Image: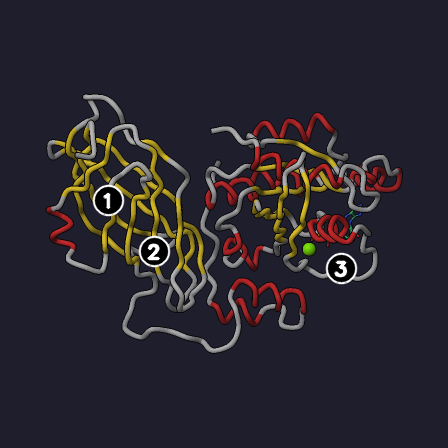
Amino acid sequence: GNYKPPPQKSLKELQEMDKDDESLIKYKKTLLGDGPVVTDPKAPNVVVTRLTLVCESAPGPITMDLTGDLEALKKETIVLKEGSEYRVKIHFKVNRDIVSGLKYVQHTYRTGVKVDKATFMVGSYGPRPEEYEFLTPVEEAPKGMLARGTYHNKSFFTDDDKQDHLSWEWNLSIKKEWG
Amino acid sequence: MQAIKCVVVGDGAVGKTCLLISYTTNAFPGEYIPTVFDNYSANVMVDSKPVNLGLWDTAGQEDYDRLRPLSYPQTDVFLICFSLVSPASYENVRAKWFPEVRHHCPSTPIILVGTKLDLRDDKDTIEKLKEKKLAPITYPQGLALAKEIDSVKYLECSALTQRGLKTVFDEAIRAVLCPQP
Ligand SMILES: Nc1nc2c(ncn2[C@@H]2O[C@H](COP(=O)(O)OP(=O)(O)O)[C@@H](O)[C@H]2O)c(=O)[nH]1
Ligand SMILES: [Mg+2]
């Protein structure tokens, strides 16, 4: 209806508040955890490692390794059968600070012009060594000879603080069959 | 068998913790009430259906606006609470809670819950509100807010007397088991 990003606060400020409140201490241990402050030096705060398209009817896997050659992905084509149901699986790692409202943004092009925009909220996550996973609700691919064709996508991962965590390009082809 | 995650949000003092403690322990606190209840799971039956309901309380303070949303991921159903004797908590749903829950989780079902139902008829509570030129939230007013936020269900309960309390959690489950695509 409106919404506005809350003021910023470090992990230190969050941990130091209500330091005598027993339930809030457990609350923080459940959400942020306790023990060794583990970090991977030489790594941004977010790092999205791969985006997969869960398609039960598809023959082989249709994924994108985001740690690899982005320039080949920019030139490659992922095939999606018209009208098929799918879910997108994201793998990523939060490093030092909390990520508020991490989200995926996509600008779709056809014949060189922008024809569609789409996004999906991944959420807010706390920093930890182990990677997180995220699946969006089931979606259906476009259907019809009007929608069938090749699209050029410009994707990126941003957040409530407008920080670009990743940007890349890839091509999508919606066809009558997997081939 | 089945796993359903439920998160409870709303203003401080509306009764989020008492609602969860009263429901899970079968007794109203009325003594020491922690700021936030610990995470517990209720093994419930809903018409031959084995459901494991994980419950999550939240720190409503503005100070935790950055930490609280970390519990939102993978939530199947939200309980947005407001006190039936607090118009301010009611408007906070419009100005804060609904926008926050929708920003982080655009498709997850919402159940609007009116708390402290036992106090709506309380003479002293009513007179105190009238002194400040306020009145309790009536059923039509609550139902009107539910429509404005497109909630799946509007329910009123009392953790103190337990009236309609169990119904709140049964509906949270039915919102997931019988959705709408
Ligand atoms: N009469 C009455 N008081 C209640 C009910 N629920 C919570 N309260 C009281 O409201 C205050 C806030 O309760 P609490 O659950 O900690 O609020 P929270 O900040 O939303 O968690 C306490 O003084 C409770 O005893 C209720 O159903 N009826
Ligand atoms: Mg509380």
Q: Is residue B82 left or right of residue B149?
A: right
Q: Amino acid at mark 1?
A: Gly
Residue B33's disc number:
3
Residue at (29, 31) in percent of width and height: A141
Q: Position of residue B122 (x, y in %)?
A: 87, 38
Q: Secondary structure at mark 3?
A: loop
Q: Amino acid at mark 2?
A: His
**Front residue (pair A109, A81):** A81
Q: Position of residue B136 (x, y in %)?
A: 76, 35
Please say if B168 is above or below A65: above
Q: Which residue is mark 2?
A: A91
Task: Check the residue under mark 2 and report the chain it is in.
Answer: A
- The image quadrant that residue A118 belongs to is top left
- Give the crowd class for mark 3: few <14, some 14-19, many >=20 residues within 10 Å: few
- Give the crowd class for mark 1: few <14, some 14-19, many >=20 residues within 10 Å: few
CA gap, disc 2 and disc 1: 19 Å
Q: Position of residue A44 (x, y in %)?
A: 30, 66
Q: Is residue A167 left or right of residue A18?
A: left
Residue A25's disc number:
none
Q: Which residue is mark 1?
A: A60
